[PDB]
Length: 186
Ligand SMILES: [Zn+2]
Image 1 (cartoon, rainbow, N blue to C red):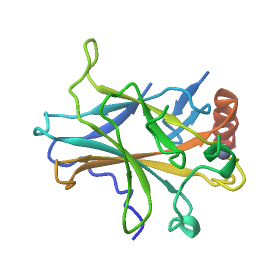
Image 2 (cartoon, rainbow, N blue to C red):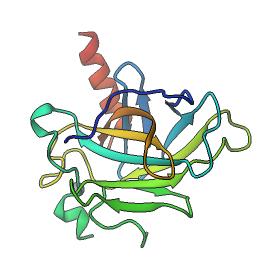
Image 3 (cartoon, rainbow, N blue to C red):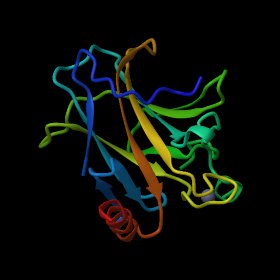
Image 4 (cartoon, rainbow, N blue to C red):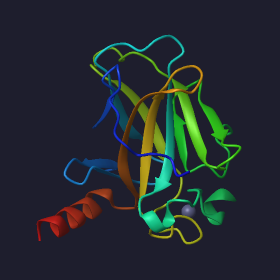
């Protein structure tokens, strides 16, 4: 079954926040980012989850007619850090404990890091993601919009919380955000 995108704050009050290489549109719930550049995603909790809590990131297609298709890199960007497998769209930057996972039954990719409390000077835990293929790449996303689903999980993989956002990976994020926002006003 297609991974759920249902927002679920859960017992710890889990939700995301956001912070031109990367720009977020709250009105569109959409992140616009350049290829392979830092995308800061903030984790907010009302209380601290138990030891061994994990944070998983996974991409799915937004449109229902493409939801059962695995999101992966196009051949050009696949065939081009030594930790992320070449097929994975999403990689984590600056984390010594990233796990790159392929689901045995769905073939979907994800990247998991341990949950850490907020870094000094912050009320939220910031994770730096990189997207390794453009929304427009033929043989990959092929202009189809995607969602990133962030799941807070216990050490066994049980769901503690879930949030999600749309992503466009593009060369001019600031300009594309304005275009899509101008389209929503019209
Ligand atoms: Zn590509």
